[PDB]
Image: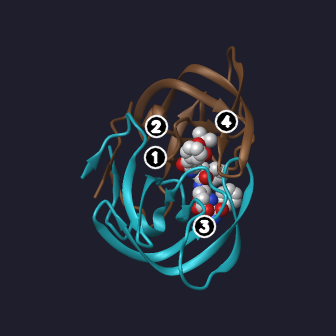
Chain colours: A brown, B cyan
Amino acid sequence: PQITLWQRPLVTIKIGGQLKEALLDTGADDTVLEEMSLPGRWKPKMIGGIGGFIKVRQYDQILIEICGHKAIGTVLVGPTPVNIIGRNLLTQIGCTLNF
Amino acid sequence: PQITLWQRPLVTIKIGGQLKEALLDTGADDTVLEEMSLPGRWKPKMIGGIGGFIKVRQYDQILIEICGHKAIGTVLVGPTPVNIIGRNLLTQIGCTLNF
Ligand SMILES: CC(C)(C)OC(=O)N[C@@H](Cc1ccccc1)[C@@H](O)CN[C@@H](Cc1ccccc1)C(=O)N[C@@H](CCC(=O)O)C(=O)N[C@@H](Cc1ccccc1)C(N)=O
């Protein structure tokens, strides 16, 4: 679909058997999700945003369905205020910016 | 133009007589620029991102040229790591996400 930006570009994602709402964020290199139930191994990692840094658990090759489109990639889980879908997954579903 | 997301969506903006590079950020409600020389009056404000909160200065009805498209709106100036063009200005240049 084509999404305009008058409202936050929130979409429905399915990950780890669960349904959640997430923000399509072109300004994020990574995908960061609020604390959640994910199976598998994971390695520590620190990331930065406006505000400072947070520590997150890095999960690789995680299946995620974004607005019906499937993608497999790195997902980070930590103290983020909102679920953020970053460029690592946005490219996977062929998402572009247009004006 | 159409912008893919394999690389950060960095564009040239002209604001306050100066040329700068900024990130098109669909995940930002506001436009936040690194410390810069801007004329006029401004109000204090606090904003949050992933990481925490920063104090910035709020300038209204400021003229900004984004990739050649002009727009007038609120711009915030503070301790941000990168210049961020948020939805308040992205809607003005008719920018949309597509997939
Ligand atoms: C997510 C991560 C992988 C860590 O990348 C970034 O932080 N990327 C940021 C760009 C960047 C690149 C390189 C280095 C540094 C920063 C930006 O795209 C992040 N987009 C969202 C991510 C986010 C949203 C919500 C919560 C936490 C984090 C954002 O900060 N949005 C801010 C942008 C600044 C602004 O608009 O003022 C925003 O809209 N903040 C709102 C909403 C809000 C309220 C309270 C807390 C947090 C957020 C606000 N008015 O404060």
Q: Characterize the local packing of mark 2: few (<14), some (14-19) or many (20 or more) Cα atoms within 10 angstroms.
A: many
Decide if residue A85 is on the left or right side of residue B2.
right
Identify the amino acid type marked 2. Arg
Q: Which residue is mark 4?
A: A47
Real-space CA distance between mark 1 and mark 3, rounded to the nearest whole angstrom: 21 Å
Q: Which residue is mark 1?
A: A26
Is the C-beta separation of discs 1 and 2 under 8 Å?
yes
Residue A56 percent coordinates (x, y): 72, 31
Task: Decide which of B74, A58 is in the foreground and name it.
Answer: B74
Disc 1 Cβ-to-ligand 1 distance below 8 Å: yes
- Is residue A95 visible in the rendered structure shown here? yes
Q: Characterize the local packing of mark 4: few (<14), some (14-19) or many (20 or more) Cα atoms within 10 angstroms.
A: some
Q: Which residue is mark 2?
A: A87
Q: How many marks?
A: 4
Residue B65 percent coordinates (x, y): 35, 68
Chain for disc number 1: A
Chain for disc number 3: B
> In the structure shown, which secondary structural element does the residue marked by tag 4 occupy?
strand
Task: Decide which of B46, A64 is in the foreground and name it.
Answer: B46
